Length: 252
Ligand SMILES: CCN(Cc1cc(Nc2nc(C)cn3c(-c4cn[nH]c4)cnc23)sn1)C(C)(C)CO
Figure 1 (spheres, rainbow, N blue to C red):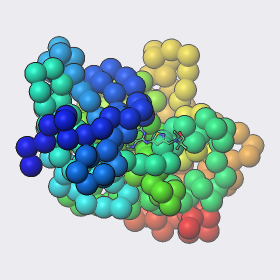
Figure 2: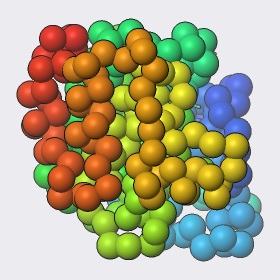
Figure 3: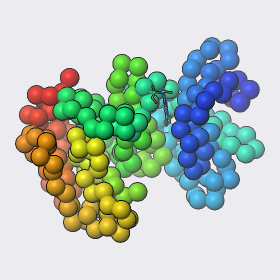
Figure 4: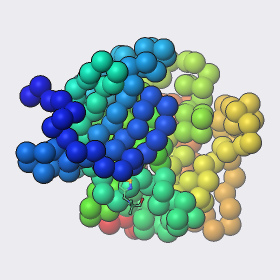
């Protein structure tokens, strides 16, 4: 399908940022409700993101999993690039965190397992996300977690492992670190290496400097400590995470 802007009715902006915005849209003929990511050619060229755009297109159109946000197609005009995406009705895990302050162990272990299954799928197809964070985690109508924004995927520093921040060689174990950061943030309400400056955060990540509040459970402390390892090869496999006692006891 060729696809033009005239085929869609644009609704409210779902999210705003650099490069463009994501809108709720409806295809005119089918009445199909979707998410329309409107990216400006001006900012894409003046940053060299053209490759990352192709990677999001290629990866998300070819990946098919219930915990991964679908990409149905794309189009462009003189000014903009339009990505036709699956719409996630229950919004971002980021927004849910702000509202709830922090999550219980049941919600956390459910989200971590859903993320691990999707990441296991990506990793079997040699796809590494590298940008796993609450803003990129979306919720379906049954409250199921879905990974979006595969732009930074290849085959703030808050969620980045020491390998990436230090500019070293990296692999699938990057997403394992990010999962450990997410697990802590879901339970605490703030990421483990948060600091008021980039220089401070960088320092905390490279040295793996984090502490647990009293309310953090032994099993949760255990899982997080296994994921948050400076050494990439020391981080467990996704199946070891899915087999973790704290995960099997609290997940759904
Ligand atoms: C207006 C009340 N809401 C609905 C809602 C639904 C949203 N859906 C989406 N939000 C954002 C940013 C991005 N989205 C994509 C996407 C990301 N990358 N590529 C595609 C896909 N679906 C969304 S936001 N709020 C509540 C009740 C969930 C709370 O807020």
